[PDB]
Length: 424
Ligand SMILES: [Mn+2]
Image (cartoon, rainbow, N blue to C red; front, side, top):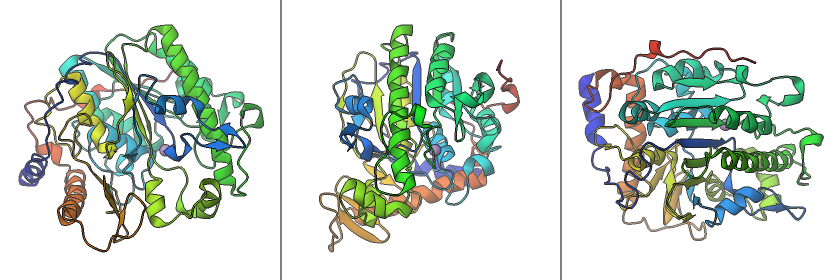
């Protein structure tokens, strides 16, 4: 079994990249705020419905002129675990499982997670905040294994009828209360806010909506417009609050969509909304879920690098100034010149700068037209994709971190973590 771990460790070595000296350590011991946008796809960015911008605040961030670096070619890599798969990957640079939920099935595995590394190396305290109860998606158990110090779950918010819609707390209340909790924290902290309102079936009380639905006739697509606007407004106000509380300028702030909100079931309506047929290649393009990052002392902009959620962990560690040579990670640092510009998807599809591989066919990204002559790097990339998924699965299925005596990681004792019931 130790041999199985050794094989994965050796496999992950070749891709390792050196940090960009422009970015290496620039955020050492600064607060890190990580903002999850439930079910958010970047087809919303710059989209108008009935003449109204769906997501005007995110549109401003996406211009690159508002201190955030926006990655328009940034993809989730989730499977059946959906939100929990995104969380898993964001904090571990590992894939979820091909079937089922890693959180639900592998919650008592040994991990060497991002929050634990930040805690150990730089004295961070890590928290998650979320307007649902802690045992949903097995978060209570998983987070203890990840070494997350605090979980402000629904018991930390007023869950009365007026404050909830669909699965739980409304995003506007959530962000307002969460900013207030964050202002009471000691630095350095690593805080992950997981939103909720922009979730299937995408329902919002009329009183809370500020944009009319689209008119495709598909209730999912049409409702998504309203919940996406609501989330955008909630986020805008959250950023305002951070500025008032002095938690904006000197924090690393990242924003990301977790996974797609609109499945292929909605191709008819999405063709109406977007004005083109949703082919398999087009659907793949629509799996862009976005990454925006603000780094203190650094200008924003637009970075066109093709990338996935696996890349976030090494990016954050390098920004902190932490040497990552001993961490078992599949991603590479977004800001490094050597960033591996190949994005595996959980189903074996993948994308690169020039082409996508979708259900056994290769398409040019320029026009989504079929490529008949196999690209020079295709075999290499296809192999990397297949092996990345297999190797990651081996870690989860073999619980392989049990066997890793890592010089740069102190084994987490999950019994040292407990999430007390909140005051509400
Ligand atoms: Mn989700």
